[PDB]
Amino acid sequence: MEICPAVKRDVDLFLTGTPDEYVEQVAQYKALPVVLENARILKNCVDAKMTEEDKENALSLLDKIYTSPLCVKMAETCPIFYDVFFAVANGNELLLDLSLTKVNATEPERTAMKKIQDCYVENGLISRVLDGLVMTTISSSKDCMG
Amino acid sequence: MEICPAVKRDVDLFLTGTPDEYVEQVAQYKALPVVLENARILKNCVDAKMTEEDKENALSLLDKIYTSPLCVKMAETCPIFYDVFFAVANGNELLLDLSLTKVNATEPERTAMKKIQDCYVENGLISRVLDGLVMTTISSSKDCM
Ligand SMILES: [Ca+2]
Ligand SMILES: [Ca+2]
Ligand SMILES: [Ca+2]
Ligand SMILES: [Ca+2]
Image 1 (spheres, each protein chain N blue to C red):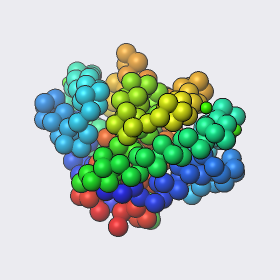
Image 2 (image 1 turned 120 degrees about the vertical axis):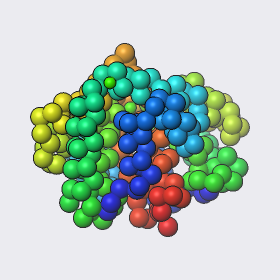
Image 3 (image 1 turned 30 degrees about the vertical axis):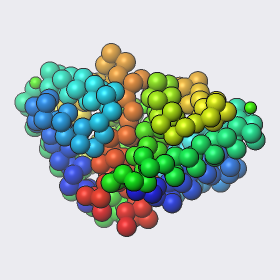
């Protein structure tokens, strides 16, 4: 089934919002100081590491995910998104690659997504409380559960 | 709001089921080989590390979570549960302790929950787990609407 719009919004802001716009949006779901602190580290990293072209390619890849049969035609909410998102957040390069292949990622798209994964990995955020909590919280919100 | 029953059931099975029963249930939500491999390692670790007494103390603590105003009276689904769960899954002992105090954990209850957290930390499993994937999948499922 299609992704919850609140989830798509969170990823869009993550990529295209200002740091404040993103972190404040996170704070609406989970206002733990550590979560907000980690969210800002991550967001500052993606802004610095990704060019405009990189962001454009991330967005086109995400559009491929949201429109994939492996997202839409499945019984539950957009399963391939969650596979990709959690591979990114926890630095699983193997599963990320496999999952990007399932949605016909271009090389520039793959490069863009790997930069986001690098921001989790290089800042030591794999074993930190962040997007497992935030993404679970958005996805299970009353907004999404309709 | 009260936790989704399917989430409560998953956690109960994690603690009290056989490894095969727990992994087969995880597979119904997310059948990725890495997820099932990790689920089994984690399950075998908790079964070996936790005494019957530890498991009882964990079940008692979860009950405190499920009945807490910080779970039930909130606008969204059992927020304190998710805080605890993700502090466990990521080996954040500070955040785990802060959350446990909120639900009036006893010392043996803290001890039991730390054993679960230790099983995530053990042998670098925290570096592997796709924490959030299974839990997001159960929590956002049609059954949880
Ligand atoms: Ca940039
Ligand atoms: Ca390029
Ligand atoms: Ca993690
Ligand atoms: Ca035992």
